[PDB]
Amino acid sequence: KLKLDAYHLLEASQSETAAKSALSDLNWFSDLADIYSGQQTMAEMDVALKAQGEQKLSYPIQGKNI
Amino acid sequence: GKIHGAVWRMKHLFATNFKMVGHPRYAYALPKNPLLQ
View 1 (cartoon, rainbow over the protein chains, first blue to last red):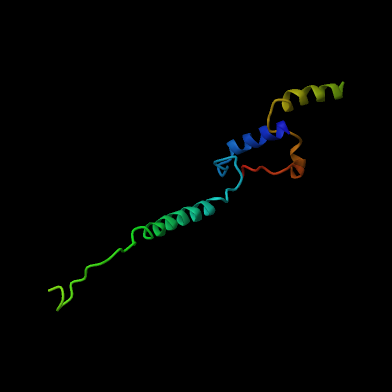
View 2: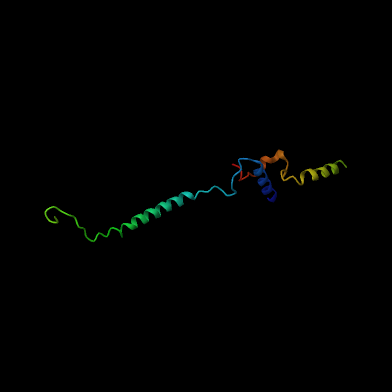
């Protein structure tokens, strides 16, 4: 096993298409993107619940306010 | 004596290569490198 690890590292050094990392295929960047977009949207729409209390309004209307 | 000479050369030429884990004619049976792709 030890010899094979050495040999693999050596042939990777000799080859040009060798992987830039010893890690296996990574497949958890999609979930990170999805949760980022989710938190972004959840904040954006937990804002306007507070920012649209809308106590009262003052519309200028012809005949009354003028 | 022939066998002695053969092994005495095998030592020097195989034991410090890092490329000959076995003989190249049987490299099909080895596992595959995870780093190649």
